[PDB]
Amino acid sequence: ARYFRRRKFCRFTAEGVQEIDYKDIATLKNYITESGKIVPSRITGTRAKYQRQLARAIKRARYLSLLPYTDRHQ
Amino acid sequence: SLSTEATAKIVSEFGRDANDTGSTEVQVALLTAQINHLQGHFAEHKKDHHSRRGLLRMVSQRRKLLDYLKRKDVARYTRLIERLGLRR
Amino acid sequence: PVIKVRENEPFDVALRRFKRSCEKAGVLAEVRRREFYEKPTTERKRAKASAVKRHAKKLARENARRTRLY
Amino acid sequence: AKAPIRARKRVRKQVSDGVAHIHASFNNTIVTITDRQGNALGWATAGGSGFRGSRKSTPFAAQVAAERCADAVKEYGIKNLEVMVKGPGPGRESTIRALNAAGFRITNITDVTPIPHNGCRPPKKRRV
Amino acid sequence: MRHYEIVFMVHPDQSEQVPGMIERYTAAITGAEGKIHRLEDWGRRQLAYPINKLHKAHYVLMNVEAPQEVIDELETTFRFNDAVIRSMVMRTKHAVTEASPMVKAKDERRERRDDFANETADDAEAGDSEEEEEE
RNA sequence: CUUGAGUCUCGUAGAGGGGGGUAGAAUUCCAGGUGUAGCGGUGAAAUGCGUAGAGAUCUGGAGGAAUACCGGUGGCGAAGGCGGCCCCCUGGACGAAGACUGACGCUCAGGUGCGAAAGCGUGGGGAGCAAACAGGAUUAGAUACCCUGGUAGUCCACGCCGUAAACGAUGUCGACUUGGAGGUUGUGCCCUUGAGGCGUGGCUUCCGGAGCUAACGCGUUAAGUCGACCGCCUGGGGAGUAC
């Protein structure tokens, strides 16, 4: 049926997690090393835009203590 | 940027009674309300120069459509500038 | 720069490949070196720049089939 | 300084676990064994191996620094280990082998080498 | 009107302050004809890092719509609220009022990982069970 | 008149501008804990710090520049220029339907506004690093280089002449010229068969054809074919000084 838009096996082999929502802790740790910082868009194969917005939403999240800012907090 | 209801008030009072935005008197009156709000902001915020560039744009297109209007009808022109309380 | 991300199965030799994702690069690499403001945008961000030698190689593969070197 | 002591048997507090700290520079390694709560139980260095130059700052001098200190603390009675690593210099892995060779487990190799939020400006050095 | 999604947490022991603060924050927003489209409390959570000491805090998503002048007075209040340790409010572009990503984790926190204490009962008096002054 | 351009509401991508809020990490600092003989620097080395207890290390607070991360061929500005996250005021550009005006156009001497960088007056701020300065090291000479000590400075706010290699050293805006594809986004269509495919706009980029170059190179974002108008150059040295 028409306008299905991500039924199956289309856009990406690897799934996109969030954009600008920032309220779940487990979705954000998808892009955080143990050194405590956001991963480049070449490694994940995000299109750059979706990453520039996430970069703000994760930083916003970090500053609210959902996430570690530094390796020293492991 | 202007409020929806300010944009409808300009259209009611200026141009013809068709309530278009397209015409030379009403484009001059729609620019005008935005120049006047920006000169409100710029009562303070005195280091904000790269946006002040935007005032000199809004002003300059208004100088071009009042230049056009005065090559045409003197009634529309002399009525507008005093009815719209414009310049000094 | 043994890098804080833990190596799959711990051993005396750190698995430096499996560890880094964006650590040390640009931040702790230019140690005892002069800091520039805007040069890093074109100086360090060289991911397109390094792909070209791989592309050149992937092009010459095809030509070796057409020449009968392959 | 050191004394000529008879063969060692001695007991101190038999604490069983520790943290090690490895402070790696360009000219040296400082290798320092602590209690988990964080108190020096002893240290050794690469520079007292008296190589001079660049040669003091090689993985084999990093190894033997680790082996002196890990040894001395057998009187403190440590049996398991963890390490924090703090510098970009060499002995990445060969220091880790000497802590294991002291007969300790060394499963947690946490690099903590601090990345300030763009901190204090470094000496300019060579004009390239 | 424009929508501003406020999320904040409070130092456990200081939570007894907030049931007084929320009833004012709602009286200034519905006093400006705004709306609260949920106001969900998630319960007490582990911080990744301490803020003003302690490794725990209690997390609240207020989910406001308000005209812009009122939100401007509210971020300054909430940032300088002494009981609040930190707070974030996000931009209008692509903003949600439904189907929360933390719906399970909220239930897990409230059910199990919580404080279980009197100082977070007060927090729940600021939570979904919101009580607010009359306009 | 629309075939040029201009305007209203809708949508979109981004570190554009100006004022507010806000956390944590190293050096640096105060206090307390633990602890013994070197640390630092480099070709190698000395000056430097240390038994008056250094060096390293742990705990808690402190302060300020700064914000490590968006990091990619991305996006924005004015070239130079812009990167923590939020809020307030707000510019400029990219799309799309409905709709309106109807050459309202191009260029711009003069012109007023506006700084990469340091320079800089008062206020604020000051942690490290550093020209000079000092001494070691070189003999290789200038206190330079190189190393250690070490100050103005760097940092913010407002303010003064806006400097350069001032940038795609490619003026402005507009018309015309085989295209495919990357990056990635409005939006029409698709099981969105893979940062995928086609319709049609968007900046941004790889390849190469017509044309253009001394040569590299450019090539639909020209350095092509052109349009008007403005800006600037006319052998070296001596002069970015002199007048």
Image (cartoon, coloured by chain):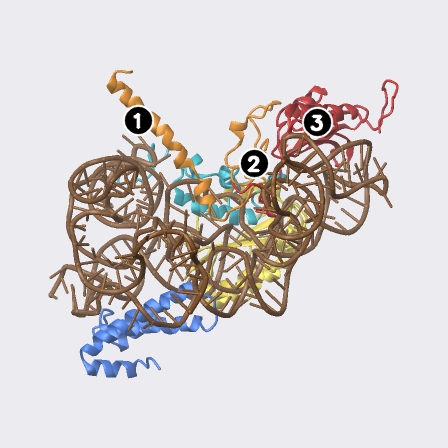
Chain colours: A cyan, B blue, C orange, D red, E yellow, F brown
Q: Residue at x 59, y 53 (%)?
A: E86
User: Residue D24: percent from the left, percent from the top?
Assistant: 66, 33
Reading the image, the residue beneath label 1 is C59
Could you tell me which quadrant the N terminus of chain D lies in? top right
Question: What's the residue at 20%, 83% (across, down)?
Answer: B75
Give amino acid for label 2.
Glu
What's the chain of the residue with tag 1?
C
Q: Is residue F64 above or below residue C30?
A: below
Bin the neighbour count of mark 3 within 10 Å (Cα to Cα): few under 14, some 14-19, many 20 and up. Answer: many
- For the point 26% across and 77% down, the residue is B14
- In the rendered image, which residue does mark 3 sit on? D81
Q: Residues within 10 Å of mark 1 (few under 14, many from 20)?
A: few
Q: How many marks?
A: 3
Q: What's the residue at 23%, 70% (across, down)?
A: B20
- Compared to residue B36, the image places residue F130 above or below, namely above
Q: Secondary structure at mark 3?
A: strand
- Secondary structure of the residue carrying tag 2 is loop
Identity of the amino acid at label 1?
Answer: Leu
Residue that mark 2 sits on = A34
Q: Is residue A73 left or right of residue D37?
A: left
How far apart are labels 2 and 3 at the CA level? 21 Å
> Which residue is more in the foreground, E69 or D20?
D20
Compute the Cα span from label 1 to label 3: 52 Å
Tell me the SS state at disc 1: helix
Q: Is residue B7 visible?
A: no
